Length: 278
Length: 278
Image (cartoon, rainbow over the protein chains, first blue to last red):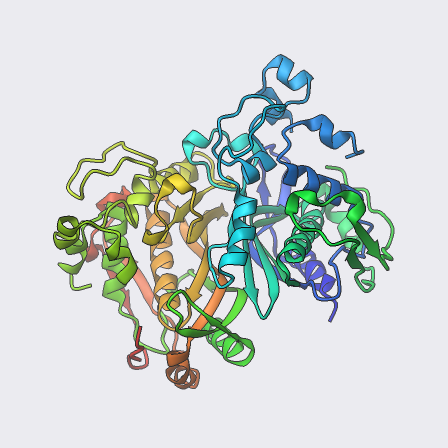
């Protein structure tokens, strides 16, 4: 049975049993604490079909994360909040320097930040490379883990908890991935994250000689913004269509060598875009 | 329907679909990656009934964790591996000094370790106190998180990933808890952890004026040791009995003030002990 159905079941469970809870803005949600869904990655790619997901943004953003960029321009230049920017100095924000955030923490966790143009080679902990090495040196490992932080949870001095914990697992030549997200916005964030970590998994599997296995998505505060209820009720009536497939078009050897042109989605036949107001 | 049934369903799923995978010893498991179960804490306490769980050990161990003890004697003195001990010097191991591990990381995360008798008041990050303050200052928070590490994952210099991530959640005057464990031994570790974090939840709820809600237990590598298969097959045939209740016997105000004598289990009618060989 089509895996997208679990996502639609979670939407329905939140509409039915979710409780009113406000977020840091004060804008309301229906909320449920604790959920999990499993999406097979074997011969299919979980890009949701009940609405069009912006695949290109998913790819270009992950690549920008992988590069460790803290330069907003490097991402927008591809064609892809208030409180984070208010922590920045004037000139750094003007030029698009985000400080020590996003993929900086994946590739240079704990490193002294200078500016977005700096050379951080070999500075801090390269969580992504460590994951890939361990898969190679000891696939049975239960600690093949990479964490991500929300930019506003700085500073690292404080030991701020992560936003996401991503665990990889290898058995029978298959790489599986579990993402734990402390909170998930079901209308907008969640579909994008599913595709994003599924793509990461495809990538790591490729360069470690494994086949993709399962993507397991686990949530703490799983929520629907009030203003997304009605568009989601309409999305719930759409029939999922077989997920597409993802193809990597050449043999790639290191995680940093992948390029947007290395990937191609195929057979993606989604229902139309649903605009949901952030 | 009785929540213990989810635990028994997970045992059965692993026996049926689990795959052979070895652990760091090389002793074998059947393994499944990614699972979740929900245990209500409302007017019941999930101490499993299909075998006797050593409640006293669960209590005394959590209290020792809460104290931040790194003194093995402080725990055994109550009546409650090879590789961790081989990292210790001679005299420190002789006297039972475990170094900067277990609840030291809950109450003094990142602090310079000296010895087990040292005064660490106000040193490092008090993750447990921070959780309790945030529940008080902002119950809607999605970052009410506390992490725990396996002792052999030192040193903290390296940014080792956590073993467990524990997230609390508050809605409608109810405190809920989700534990993410990178690996779980279903025969021995898992029942103990369920009770342990359910007890923690009861404790925090008590001193924050809330009612216990749900305990959500999430696993990465969920596994059964080969030598536990047969005793577990027998446990699977036992009918769960209504979970007991937990009673806190006086009004307690700070997390550090709880004592073993403050708690009483009631109505606990378990099937007999099952001895499972570690």
